[PDB]
Amino acid sequence: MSVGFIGAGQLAFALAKGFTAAGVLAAHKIMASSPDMDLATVSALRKMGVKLTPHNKETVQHSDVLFLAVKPHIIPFILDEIGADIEDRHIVVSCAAGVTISSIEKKLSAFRPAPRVIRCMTNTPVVVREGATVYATGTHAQVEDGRLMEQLLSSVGFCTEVEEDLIDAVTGLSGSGPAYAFTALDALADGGVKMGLPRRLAVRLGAQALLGAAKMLLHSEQHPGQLKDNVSSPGGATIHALHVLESGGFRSLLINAVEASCIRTRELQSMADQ
Amino acid sequence: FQSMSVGFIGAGQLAFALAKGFTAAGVLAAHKIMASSPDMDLATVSALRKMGVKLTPHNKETVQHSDVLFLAVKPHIIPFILDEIGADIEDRHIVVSCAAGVTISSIEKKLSAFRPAPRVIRCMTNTPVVVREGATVYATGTHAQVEDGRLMEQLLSSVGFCTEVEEDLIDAVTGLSGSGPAYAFTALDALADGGVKMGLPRRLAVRLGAQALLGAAKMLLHSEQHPGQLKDNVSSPGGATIHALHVLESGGFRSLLINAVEASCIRTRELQSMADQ
Amino acid sequence: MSVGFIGAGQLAFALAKGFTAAGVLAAHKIMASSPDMDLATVSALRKMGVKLTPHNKETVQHSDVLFLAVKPHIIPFILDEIGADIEDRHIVVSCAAGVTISSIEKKLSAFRPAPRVIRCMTNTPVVVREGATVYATGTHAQVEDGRLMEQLLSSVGFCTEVEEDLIDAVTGLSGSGPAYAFTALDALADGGVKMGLPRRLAVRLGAQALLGAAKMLLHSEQHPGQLKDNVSSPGGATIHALHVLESGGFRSLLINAVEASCIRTRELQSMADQE
Amino acid sequence: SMSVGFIGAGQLAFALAKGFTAAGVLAAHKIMASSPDMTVSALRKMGVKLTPHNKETVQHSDVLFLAVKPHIIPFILDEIGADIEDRHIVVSCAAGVTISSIEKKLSAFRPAPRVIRCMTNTPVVVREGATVYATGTHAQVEDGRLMEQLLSSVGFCTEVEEDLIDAVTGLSGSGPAYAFTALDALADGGVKMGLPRRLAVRLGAQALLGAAKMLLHSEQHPGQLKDNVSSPGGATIHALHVLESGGFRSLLINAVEASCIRTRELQSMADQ
Amino acid sequence: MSVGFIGAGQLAFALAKGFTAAGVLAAHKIMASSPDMLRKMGVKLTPHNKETVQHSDVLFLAVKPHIIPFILDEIGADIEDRHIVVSCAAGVTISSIEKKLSAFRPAPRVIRCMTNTPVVVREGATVYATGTHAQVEDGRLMEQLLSSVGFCTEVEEDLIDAVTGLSGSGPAYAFTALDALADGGVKMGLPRRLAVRLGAQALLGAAKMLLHSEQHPGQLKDNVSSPGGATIHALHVLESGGFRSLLINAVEASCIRTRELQSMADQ
Ligand code: PRO
Ligand code: PRO
Ligand code: PRO
Ligand code: PRO
Ligand code: PRO
Ligand code: PRO
Ligand code: PRO
Ligand code: PRO
Ligand code: PRO
Ligand code: PRO
């Protein structure tokens, strides 16, 4: 199997870092192309052993699975450039937020019939092999292509198939999720610093607390409210802190965030289709 | 130290999580663990019973059984325990208090009445030790030999992060990583509600939000970059993420988490001043 | 067994009505006294068959179990009024919010030693036999007294023993709780009316919704968050309504309420201990 | 002799099947449930015949509950519309879905379908549901009476005009979730003031149940019952004040309104 | 004079109770009809709307606003020259009513009014507008009949939706305020029964003061508040919550909804 990346941004580096750390891909079996060959991420890939080239056509010719790791508004221009170079062996995997399978297939179909397209939403934690990935299969993605992509993406985190009409909501939850967590961890650390902890120790403790709680939930058959109840001793410090969260509408803010991200994702695609 | 006996006074959530973590790490055999509780009809008690942990209603037997003795009872019960088993403390014992707010000097004062130089360690840990990803800090008491702290850190590092701190930091650690898991559980419930509002099935929404949090936290622990920089790397210009971050800022999301750490730390200090009275 | 009520107000009527509906006591075996024999509760008690008298001493002499259903600050004047009339057979059951076992025992002990005192916190839904009652036992309240107490009060709702130091918080939750629900049901009916429902129907539907939800939780081994998860279909009407509750800090308001009730209960006793 | 079927085996189908069996109005073997992916070990232990095929449930049943997500109703109706017989009563439990849209789809197969629309809720599982129904064009006077007797066995039930069901959805349909949220928060409050969690949850739920039963059995306004519990200067009126200061009442009006408005939106999307 | 009511809800009961208490009409000269079947007063009843029409000279339409067009088409052919039709329905225009009734007989005599429930204690607040064929004697007879149970004055029809938001919905604003003022009295230690009576008397007394005064309500507010005193402290916490803006919001919200409802009726 030969994997290629169109784009050499953060997600291209993240996935190639995870894939090779997982030992599922030899770094030299991965080719990446960038329009800005002086990127910080392009220099990192060259050290890993990832083959590099400025021409997207080189990436198409050298790969079987083809990740589109470009900005959403760049997808149509990439598809126009490489469309005549797609062969029957290709699986085209768009990672762009919002961009639909139908729009990709329509562009590629003008060149050759029956493009094999898969759409996915992943996130940056694939770089430490703890990503969250969903994918949906296009019209001509044979039953094997989805299972192949799930095997590949499972090596860097959780991965499952969804209906495509859920991917915008997933984007608002696990696609944007890490940024919510980085904000929360920065603020939790400021809280620790306010109460007298050194900054380095506060970041470590807050981050370990979030990782541990999330692992607990994933490994538990209990509701998050039940796990919350087990932390909060009657009259104790935790339930006092939980109350001030509630007084600020903490829960509503995170609902607001998933909603706003999902709505914007739909808007960006409506702008694309217009 | 695979011949050491560990005892828990208290058989609640913290005793169970530490006992599960320790045996899951395979650093202690479950039958080498004894726990004592005044209420035996607790769910955690039946759990400990099935693990193979020895259960007893008498704190004295836990003391005679143990080398390391965790005090995993509610903070205001600690002085009652110290009076009960203080005459049973022997030279071999290391007493590890897990009670929020209770000071090393308050423990050493009660125990020194019975026999001098009690070996006392105060720690603050959290429930994720049950999946070996806890966050533990400890402070060493007056007669806690350098070897006792090193033993303590070796033991608690088997179930997550562990480091020594000065004792005057522990109340603030309590508000951050002690209470921290409940902030995350609340956030994960809410994020899952957000996914459900936007059309996702609950089970999938819970899993995605939890995986997102775990992945982000691991990224930061493995990164040499500021969390603000990692946040910047996620936010595409004009995109969905920066739109979501704006609505969090408009609600004072950052300030609420600062409020929580402060409120928990302050309450922890209050609990000790009520005991001190 | 003969039961007495010092005070003939809402709580005495509620308990007496539930007891006689449960069939654990005949109405003629209940005596109630009140400093004001013109209340609507007194007229309802008379029609029920309850004996009514203006003299608290008559109630003490009639009864085996003696409930103190007066306002909290009236208790010290009651205990001084009838302390010398307390006999060995009496179990004194204080229903007054805040008033501690120690304060009652201290005033009664000046007359005869070893008064049998129970402190309880109940609520008005005992009148339909669905109350929430907790009780704590005094120093001389033998094991049979609490067991008898729990048997009597279990006939009109949930009843369990607690440590006394929990009762002020219970007062904030189940003691004041019915008022929180009456407010909620008034508001839910207003929302139904805003959206086009007749008032009478909106009140019936909202009350039925709250009753069934509460019974579901009581009969389930599942967390209330899981039950909430079960009713909220993805993208649906319920999760949209829950969002607007969260945006107003709905959860925090109810936490505020239990806290404020409990704190006030503590303040009231501190003022009494000062007097 | 009446046979009941369920197209969908979700929360609502399980809840109605559980309440109906607890009520003894239906033997569990007279109940069939169908789902694309299945609660399977639950209903089989309960005695409910299960099957993956919707046509089997139609062929087995006299009364046919449609307990699928609202946007799945058109695909169900087109799948089994040709299997509907004269004996069938079709009871839609989907939120927002109109009688006229069900009758329109079914009338393409056979004239005069007997359609009833209802809005019920999950406490039917403990036989304390709140149910309203509206009768369709060809639902004879007998069908609404039969539906009301069946659903009255698992809680409150009454006929309404169909134009009220979206509002009912926002009140008693979504209501239980408002209650579970409140009970979780009331228990947090008890825990903050020192109660064990288990006991706090029990006391809060009992208080809610008792208050609701009081109102249902009382000839008085809920504000009068609220007055009767708040003694002057006491703990309750202090607690009521902090609820008023947060706009507690307005939040519950907001919820009923938001649920009703969404229910209308869900149908306007299906009609489009 | 013969007075009839179509609809038998709160408004019909309020007006009938006020009219008889005022002594302008004997109860037996009044007839009310309703589909959902006052009798103790002596007011004749019937389920048929045509009977009320054939009995009455003045015909009050106290039905819900969305039922008015159904009533007009039901009784339109029985409207006769002697009839004055008085619509109490919120929002419903004189022109919509006259258009309905003119398809049966020309020049219907139509009056539109906005009253409120305190007519039952003869302290209502009523405004009315006269239709195209309401001879000037019909407005005078209307103001005469309605002044016996409260304030009554003629207005241009385009003000009635605003009036509805002020004095039509206003009693509900007051009942909410009186319930809350009572909760305040109870919080501060008063018995509930006494707190209700004191708050209501305070509100009644201040309203009457303003009505019998030539002074601005701010001037009367100044006369109550002594410097540094309890009242001015209380007014501050009202201002801090934006109390004034809430009542403006209420009048506006009610007026706007009244217009929405009529716009839905027109379409
Ligand atoms: O997700 C989608 O839309 C397509 C349809 C069936 C499988 N994948
Ligand atoms: O709630 C409390 O008081 C303890 C301290 C941190 C975890 N739980
Ligand atoms: O932090 C404390 O209190 C002691 C002093 C040095 C080590 N541990
Ligand atoms: O911000 C955006 O548009 C994408 C969505 C998840 C991460 N970046
Ligand atoms: O709770 C109390 O005050 C006492 C102590 C043991 C039984 N009742
Ligand atoms: O959320 C919804 O759309 C439906 C309405 C009541 C229960 N669930
Ligand atoms: O409620 C409805 O819309 C129809 C009309 C009469 C009976 N059911
Ligand atoms: O209002 C009070 O003070 C008492 C305590 C709970 C019920 N009523
Ligand atoms: O107020 C109106 O609309 C009409 C015009 C003059 C008299 N009545
Ligand atoms: O302002 C004051 O202090 C007095 C009290 C009632 C009226 N004015």
Image (spheres, coloured by chain):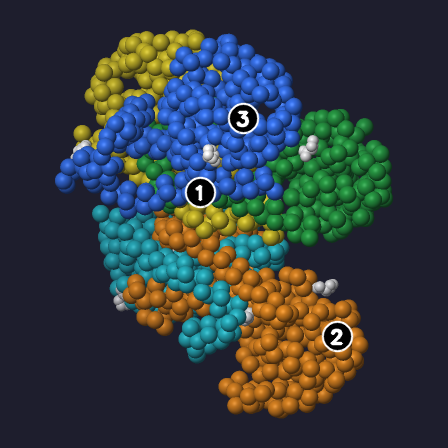
Chain colours: A orange, B cyan, C yellow, D green, E blue
Q: Amino acid at mark 1?
A: Ala
Q: Nearer the viewer, residue B43 or B133?
A: B133
Q: Nearer the viewer, residue E160 or B15?
A: E160
Position of E206 with respect to D251 (left or right) is left
Percent of width and height locating residue E41: 48, 11
Position of C90 with respect to D211 (left or right) is left
Q: Which residue is mark 1?
A: E253
Tell me the mark number nearer the camera, choosing from 2 and 1. Answer: 1
Disc 1 versus disc 3: distance between alpha carbons?
32 Å
Q: Which residue is mark 2?
A: A116
Some atom of ligand 9 lies within 8 Å of the CB belonging to the residue at label 3: no
Q: Amino acid at mark 3?
A: Arg
Can marks 2 and 1 be said to lie on one chain? no
Tell me the mark number nearer the camera, choosing from 3 and 2. Answer: 3
Q: Is residue C85 above or below residue A124?
A: above
Image quarter in which the N terminus of chain A is found: bottom right
| Residue at x 52%, y 87% (from the top left corner) | A39
Q: Which mark is residue E109?
A: 3
User: Which chain is mark 3 on?
Assistant: E
User: Which chain is mark 1 on?
Assistant: E
